[PDB]
Amino acid sequence: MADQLTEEQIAEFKEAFSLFDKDGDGTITTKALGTVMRSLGQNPTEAELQDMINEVNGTIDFPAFLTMMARKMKDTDSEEEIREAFRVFDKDGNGYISAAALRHVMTNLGEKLTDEEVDEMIREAGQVNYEAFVQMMTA
Amino acid sequence: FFQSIQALMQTCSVLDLNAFERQNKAEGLGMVNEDGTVINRQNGEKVM
């Protein structure tokens, strides 16, 4: 989704795009977009900038820049989700949730998971390590 | 009146295996991938 970023982040991106596209026509050149991203702290490499441009006249509009940045936002969200999955077991401090702890966590998740689903997830992969839980969640 | 009632009662659908399978597969996903809940209240049942 294009609205993955927070409201403050979206406002900052819009301000940067407006500053880069000072002509008021919305279209912003690739060099201008890169300069705006660097000024906002999201300075990407030349190959990364080319890949982002390809994924998203010689100019890119503000909605196009938002769509391109949405990919990085989704990647950051996925990384945060992976970190949360890895640290779910480390939250208790032991680092290796037991079978009862894993069942309790699965019940607390409430993602339409029954006893059979929990058993299948455990079998797919007896204490469950944090790394093992993260790998199972990644699938 | 008779023609309208015939059309209305012929329009009514019947049980479909494909529709039931589609409903089951859709219900297989409990919620959205991220930042969303698949309530499916409007969809309800794909058949009947």
Image: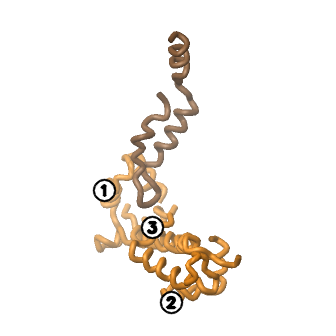
Looking at the rendered structure, the number of numbered marks drawn on it comes to 3
Amino acid at circle 3: Val
Residue visible at 39% across and 64% down in the picture = A128
| The one of A126 and B3 positioned closer to us in this rendering | B3
* Residue depth check, mark 3 versus mark 1: number of the one nearer the observer: 1
Residue under pointer 1? A108
| The one of B14 and A16 positioned closer to us in this rendering | A16
Q: Earlier in the sequence, mark 2 or mark 1?
A: 2
Q: Secondary structure at mark 1?
A: helix
Q: In the rendered structure, are the residues bearing label 2 and label 1 in contact, judged by CB atoms less than 8 Å apart?
A: no
Q: What chain does badge 2 belong to?
A: A
| The one of A52 and A31 positioned closer to us in this rendering | A31
Residues packed near mark 3 inside 10 Å, few (<14), some (14 to 19) or many (20 plus): many
Residue visible at 60% across and 86% down in the picture = A32
Residue under pointer 3? A134
Residue visible at 52% across and 33% down in the picture = B20
Up-down relation of residue A119 to residue A81 (above or below):
above
Q: Colour of chain A?
A: orange
What is the spatial separation of the Cα atoms under label 2 and label 1, in whole angstroms?
A: 43 Å
Q: Position of residue A103 (x, y in %)?
A: 33, 55
A64 on left or right of A113: right
Q: Earlier in the sequence, mark 3 or mark 1?
A: 1
